[PDB]
Image (cartoon, rainbow, N blue to C red; front, side):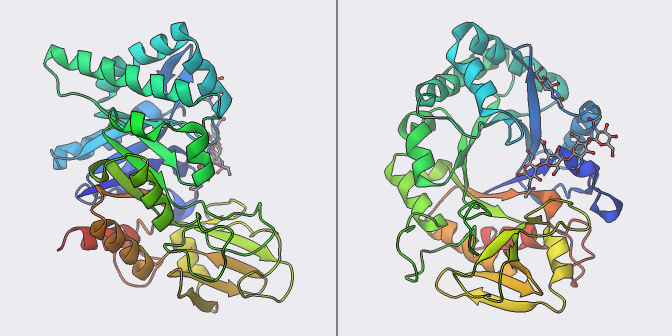
Length: 361
Ligand SMILES: CC(=O)N[C@@H]1[C@@H](O)[C@H](O[C@@H]2O[C@H](CO)[C@@H](O[C@@H]3O[C@H](CO)[C@@H](O[C@@H]4O[C@H](CO)[C@@H](O)[C@H](O)[C@H]4NC(C)=O)[C@H](O)[C@H]3NC(C)=O)[C@H](O)[C@H]2NC(C)=O)[C@@H](CO)O[C@@H]1O
Ligand SMILES: *[C@@H]1O[C@H](CO)[C@@H](O)[C@H](O)[C@H]1NC(C)=O
């Protein structure tokens, strides 16, 4: 069973206890840790922050304690133009230059693979993602001839049906990637003027226009499209999405005024870390969608949709019963990594809980 965990760069800036460094990462926790995100410059893979070389270095020392742990660097990300990627991929002289530069860079900084996080290809780009993936793997294969262990190649694939059809040739890219992580955590958002969960596990016979907006459907669609189970990985979020209520309506369907106020430590409209959530839960109203199997809480005029140990364990049995390759978690630095905000003295509660299901029968 694979356990892919993302660590984000910008998480070093968070203040106080919010601060997170590859340091904090427990080396036996995951099977793969992915550094997010690399930049592209002069058509070549390159660092993003000033001190990335240091952090890459810190993160790859974990391998001293755990020789079986693999690490990957992710290119792309949301704060990276889709457009920029699209430009490098359609012109063969630029794509090749991008391609040729990756093995050397990864080898220098001691990564084991590259993660493609192109969010998201347009309908005109599908043909080009496919070429990118194909040529990239071909280069990785050619580089192994030099007697090194072949680099891994993976991709982050969004989970809304429409998004998938528009830009991903699932049948084609799966033969070339080592694993695909499904971002099953973005099914709702402030962009819809009502309250709703972003990572429901099942459809829940409540509403029926968006029957394609849950992990279960996404996982089946990918399977029908030709991705083998032994390569699909289900994404499980460790943050929650917040919303400012526009009324006193707190139940399903309730109206919204916009995203929720920022967290003391993550400072971002509409997002909360699990550790900020554990604090929020005091004097909050506990609620849970029984059909969909995920919780939400509300207090004053704030309404938060999130995941806890029960939900995340539930998601893990799902992937086990469908025989998927494993689980991916976004992201380690949003979990209770110090282990001192969520009561019980356990660090990485959400992630350990997933591991526990994965590690048994
Ligand atoms: C659920 C989840 O995890 N969501 C994530 C989402 O949060 C990610 O996005 C990011 O948004 C925040 C703002 O909301 C960005 O933070 C800044 O990061 C930059 C560095 O790139 C910092 O600049 C530094 O500030 C210090 C001063 O303290 C200086 O010393 C530095 O030199 C300066 N950098 C320079 C010189 O330019 C800045 O301080 C950070 N401040 C914040 C807002 O905390 C963050 O960059 C941004 N991520 C990206 C890649 O843009 C998103 C990532 O793509 O994924 C999610 O959806
Ligand atoms: C990333 O690369 C682009 C392309 O050169 C460059 O424009 C930018 O300065 C880099 N971004 C950051 C913040 O490092």
